[PDB]
Image (tube, rainbow over all chains, first blue to last red; front, side, top):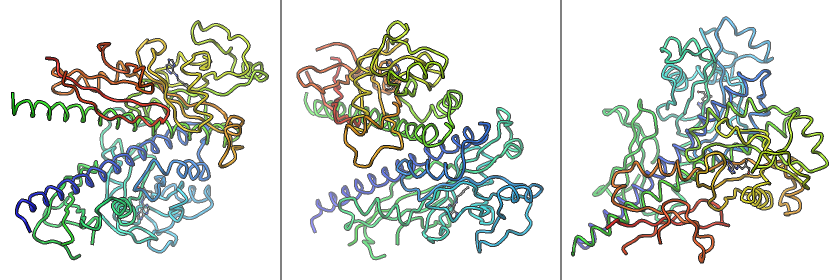
Length: 266
Length: 263
Ligand SMILES: C/C(=C\CNc1ncnc2[nH]cnc12)CO
Ligand SMILES: C/C(=C\CNc1ncnc2[nH]cnc12)CO
């Protein structure tokens, strides 16, 4: 009611929204760094070491025990690069056929594939699935290996849970990767892709829901990579259309842009 | 005077709080990644048989993930060796367990904690019995008894003589019961994943580069003993100051940051 109270009413919204934005950004950052460590893990213990020290069992165990290191991630998995020329050989050795993600059926002929060979049990259904048979995942895989850095997809509904989230992807390179490599060289030296599923719908709601004063505030997160086409990353809704605040978000991928919008319930 | 006194205070609080936050977050990040290393050793060295990790692999993985541990000068893994195992152990590694102070053959002890894995930045730790140093020894004991990360008091590290603190995680054998007793933890102890927080150098590099650093004096104290505050960072000096909170993760220890203006 009061006018001076309105000022403080905004100050509160600003503080609450900014804090929640910092928490989200930090938690995301922490998870990205540990996934990065997993990519290095696979490179060191699977490819560099002879013989490999990593099988599905080992990957499952280590990732499970370190799940607390990756908050906001529902699971991690490693997909290996497989060129069509190698497919038969790859499938005979693993004793299973590469499958599409849409139906889990034997994949048709493609130039290359990205089937998951290692997976955290939380996402064990990814095993043998070709990560390139999904458009979001395919684009992430390409940009990942071309840039040599972590990358994020647009928000989309994940496999099995259908939860709205985003996928994080790190490239894994063979030792043959030249220093100061070109994009062409990065592609030629690609071994595989370490991916993480950011279950935003479930895990972000869980983080926010526990915070004091949550019932009083409405929190929305947007992918604004495309100015004219903002994509809802999190949030549903009846709210206070008179006042709002925009908090800054940086999820680490220069190719994507995000922001948080907060309002009062009423 | 006088409204400037207020701003002068508000600036000190803000400057000190931010430095404290930065310091705590960096420490926290380093601790979490050392925890992952402890888990890594458990899985690859003990859960897998034969062992699927060695000095070569440890050195590579820790070097490549060095960025993950901002305030650590290096990390290493010391394995638990009881005396009756010493001959076999030394014969297997082809070296003798050495003392920390002189690097001489260790006298007979009930047990030892020789480093078998090391990041090349602390390669000199290899074969050294971490129990032959009091700070390290106590850290090792409290680590395996509590089952959680532990920190030492500030003390000068090997080789560099830089003032800092050691972080230690316990690594347990699979034979560790759940909801175990201290006696059970000790019996299941496999080794100790340790890291050296080079405060004197790395913290200085962290804070000394911040804008306005020349205007304020910054101290970090180990106040585990209120009557005997230990300097962890800053000079050895005893009006307008401010105390910023610090939580390094070890309930056994207490810390605080103190910021003050020069004039
Ligand atoms: C394995 C990798 C990505 C992981 N992607 C996903 N991980 C988990 N669920 C999903 N639904 C759609 N894509 C995913 C490699 O880039
Ligand atoms: C390997 C472990 C401790 C590491 N301790 C040290 N690590 C590095 N430099 C030092 N100087 C004195 N002690 C140290 C196990 O707790």
